[PDB]
Image (cartoon, coloured by chain):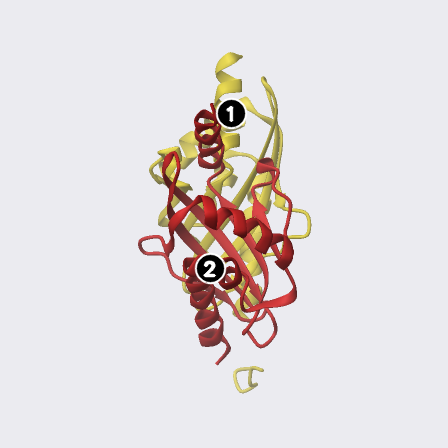
Chain colours: A red, B yellow
Amino acid sequence: NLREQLIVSAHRWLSTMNDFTPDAMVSHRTEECVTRPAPRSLGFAPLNNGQLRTFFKTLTAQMKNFNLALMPGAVPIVDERLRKVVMHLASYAEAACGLYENEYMVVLTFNEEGTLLRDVIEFADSDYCVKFAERQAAAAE
Amino acid sequence: GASMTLNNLREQLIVSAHRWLSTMNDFTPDAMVSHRTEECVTRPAPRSLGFAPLNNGQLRTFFKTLTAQMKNFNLALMPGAVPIVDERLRKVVMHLASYAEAACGLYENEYMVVLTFNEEGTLLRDVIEFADSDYCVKFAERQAAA
């Protein structure tokens, strides 16, 4: 059943982000998979798997105990025709300048079998991203 | 008629999602709260913006303010985005861009919206509006300065 497979693959993706190693975080993707941070005002460019893995190499060295979880009451929204899963998520991590806590709407798109990830839209709380960058800059001096 | 067999809830949900967009672009308070169930709320997100949900009456009052302060409003799918439809849950997800003209200049926001419809797919029963919160905060600043 396609709906069940898409949900399994969406939970697997969540699991690989929580593994929080660069190899695990880019696992189970198609060759041409693209990760697209959003909203556009953040100015973060999309990433292929190699660009993403390189970014995670530094991310996983600067943050610890990353956790991604469904928001309370949130469920996977599944479009079987488009092989898409939408999830409302919360993140937590530990940084040099304290705690990181954010909120996201994520759109996952899978291949036609529903077994490999081929697109991610990661729509973050941009106010929090901006504030966190201010915190990092504050620690820089 | 009744003895013909069927092979279209997805198409119905897409029609109602596009109707929601078109009535938003009509940009009158009445149009902007139309085709909703009696208990429907609009839920601003992320939580950091600090806004509680608005019921139909609260939302109409909000839009009376908004339609008095902005001109040439447009709400539309982001470039290249299409509606994402979960027939089982009666949900439609849309990545949207807004445009309007205010006293302080342009209003240009971006959202991920989750519409939930009633079982028949003909009335909106819930909206989550996940906004670009940095833009929201900056636009509040720009408005205060003016």
Q: Chain of mark 2?
A: B
Numbered disc 2: secondary structure: strand
Percent x, y of residue B101 = 62, 25
Between residue A118 and residue A4, name the one nearer to us.
A118
- Residue located at (42% from left, 61% from top): A19
- Specify the quadrant that holds the N terminus of chain B: bottom right
**Circles 2 and 1: CB atoms closer than 8 Å:** no
- Residue located at (47% from left, 74% from top): A3
Mark 1 residue type: Lys
The answer to whether residue A107 is visible is yes
Q: Residues within 10 Å of mark 1 (few under 14, many from 20)?
A: few
Numbered disc 1: secondary structure: helix
> Tag on residue B138?
1
Side (left or right) of B104 relative to B51: right
Side (left or right) of B143 relative to A90: right
Between residue B112 and residue B40, name the one nearer to us.
B112
> Tag on residue B109?
none
Query: From the viewer's perspective, is residue A4 above or below residue A24?
Result: below
The answer to whether residue B55 is visible is no
Query: From the viewer's perspective, is residue B24 above or below residue B70?
Result: below
